[PDB]
Image 1 (cartoon, rainbow over the protein chains, first blue to last red):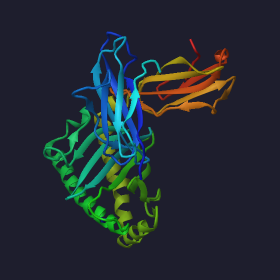
Image 2 (image 1 turned 180 degrees about the horizontal axis):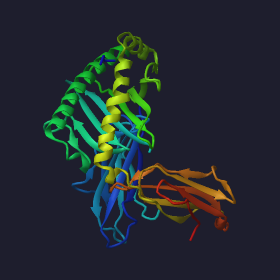
Image 3 (image 1 turned 180 degrees about the vertical axis):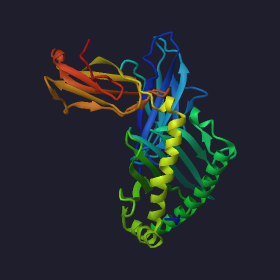
Length: 4
Length: 99
Length: 275
């Protein structure tokens, strides 16, 4: 999952 | 954001002099999470007071449960002292057994 | 039913120590059953509820590894957030996440759940469609457009729609004696002077579970909304919860007021007056  | 803590002081069971109980201090609705909480016995801090693991609600604000065993007597006065960046001075809420 | 599982993750960055504090807590039907704190002895997820003890070493290790993964995820997100908001350095910030799933009485999925917050305010959240995002503000639009390009949604949905439900099932079967129980509320009313010709009436509900409950004051057959204080349901300290509802009543007319308690475990609502 990609970070903010 | 900054949310001042909501404080509630109370006993697990309806208090009864001479009968072992539990003194609770529920601090909640606060943010950020660094917070100071003490329980008082006749104005004095009580050693070894246990408390819950940090948590938070739907609205993102934090809450903790502070407690300690005690046996309520006629004249013993209890209270909860709470300090948080939103307060200019520690907030003291007295335990009213017959709320 | 309903039923739910939720993981509440908090990360607080501290000055001088470029490693954020990461705290994750898991709940089932709102009861804590697992927890991980990076400020612990040897960070690792730990059983919070008895029915979690039957989990073997493999369960913990895997769970703990993910936590090590989230510490990282939260470390970078914080750093990125710090920028989006043109914030300084050496300060303290909070990033929080809520994730989970709900089920109806039938145990099928009712809703997927995923949402984030920064500094105590909504940041970005997955929509109930588990395909679109709602960004609280400007900066969140950056994360939004950034997450739409990579298709983050589909993955979360995969989890929330499947894995989440599966794990919830197991937890539900393992501790059903604990979770599926209901403790009916015990009620009573207290009296307290408020003003010259004004009185305070307090309705109590104690030892109930789950925490959900409804308290009302009524005149004849209509509920009272004015000068009626409702306090936040609180934990008894032993798994049960407490709450009360107060209303300011004219001195001498108390008898025409009634309290009512509605709760899952009650055959029928509790109705009582002052005495």
